[PDB]
Amino acid sequence: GGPDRAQLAVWANEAIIATYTFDYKNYMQQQKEIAKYFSADGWIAYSKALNQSKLPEVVQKNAYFVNAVATEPPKLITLDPTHWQAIMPILVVYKNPQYEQKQNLKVVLGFTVASPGQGVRGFSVTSLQSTPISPPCQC
């Protein structure tokens, strides 16, 4: 009964990773595709934050290729029958042939059942918040 935890966890990971997968060359077309994962209001907020961070300008000046990977599986919470939140730590790499830049982020993803013709595979990002964190450890 209810949604599939695996379906929600897989989508939340895909949505977070898609958002942090772009490069200086095709940036605009890639962002247009990333936008499909979001709700209209969700995108307006995210794009506002992304442009204000001036990350698009950094990516251009440094000819970067941005990629990301989860450092831990996402944590899911149900806010209402159609609204969920995923908390997932990721590693983002800003790479070019000369050098690299790495960053660990805590991504808080608010998401819901997509509205007609919108979202990706039936879900829409309502909010994406990322705060820088410490890297994880191992033994």
Image: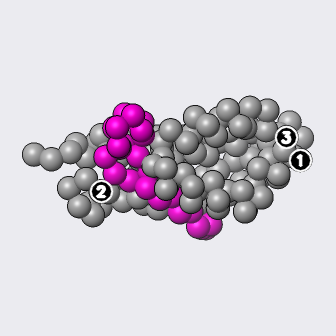
From the viewer's side, name the closer residue of 73 and 76: 76
Q: Which mark is residue 61?
A: 1
Segment tinted magenta in the rendering: 111-139
- N-terminal of the two: label 1 or label 2? 1
Count of number-bearing discs: 3
Residue 55 vertical position relative to residue 29 in the rendered view, above or below? below
The verdict on residue 122 being magenta is yes
In the visual, does 61 lie left or right of 64? right
Q: Which circle, 1 or 2, is nearer the viewer?
A: 2
Q: Position of residue 43 (x, y in %)?
A: 54, 51
Instruction: Name the amino acid type tagged 1.
Output: Lys
Please state which amino acid type lies under the numbered disc 3.
Ala
Residue 72 vertical placement versus 79 (above, below): above
Query: What residue appears at the point 70 percent right and 43 percent down from the top-left corner?
Result: 66
Q: CA distance from mark 1 to mark 2?
A: 38 Å
Name the residue tied to disc 2.
83
Image mark for residue 63:
3
Q: Residue at x 72, y 56 (%)?
A: 51
**Which residue sits at x=36%, y=59%?**
85
Label 2 element class: strand
